[PDB]
Amino acid sequence: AMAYDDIVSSMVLELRRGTLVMLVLSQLREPAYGYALVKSLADHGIPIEANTLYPLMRRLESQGLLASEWDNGGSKPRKYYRTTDEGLRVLREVEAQWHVLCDGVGKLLETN
Amino acid sequence: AMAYDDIVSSMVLELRRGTLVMLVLSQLREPAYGYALVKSLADHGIPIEANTLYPLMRRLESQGLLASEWDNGGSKPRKYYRTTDEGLRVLREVEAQWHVLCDGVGKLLETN
Image (cartoon, rainbow over all chains, first blue to last red; front, side, top):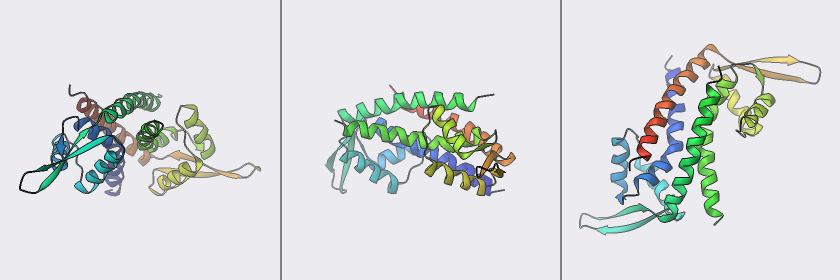
């Protein structure tokens, strides 16, 4: 009724979430402040809260997959982040498996 | 080292999880016992524990998206489940948005 719309939204939201790490690693192949990444994702049609995004980025930093740097610009300091050599390796692997997954899922859904 | 393999596995595992509800609704367009669905998914290359699968199916039942029936066959009773008219509606919507999502994600990853 509106319950059904709510069910659909949230199942679409789930699908989107799964893809975010990959999108973050991909974006941060160019060094960026978290705020910039936020607007960069929403600009490409992918909404993400700072409250989700920032913990995800630090967790990726703790994995060796992002590295970070402080910029002092008098406004305040802000970190920028960049995908490391290992992060790109991880990204490229996951992406290739994602594509296989998508074709496998597609075929299974098409059994008609 | 093996940490990296573990990071990759789990990011691939995440991607797979997102797709499961859709696969369950799709499979249960033919009535099936949970045990059958378990083996049916692992047969198509998608591993799922009964411990995850069964709560997901009841939650889908509580949404009006699966309905269920008891079979008494003397071994014991077992429920079978089937996708309802609303479930197929929900499935077909999510799937169409999933495809758009995949093409959007693909293009974003290919910016080179």
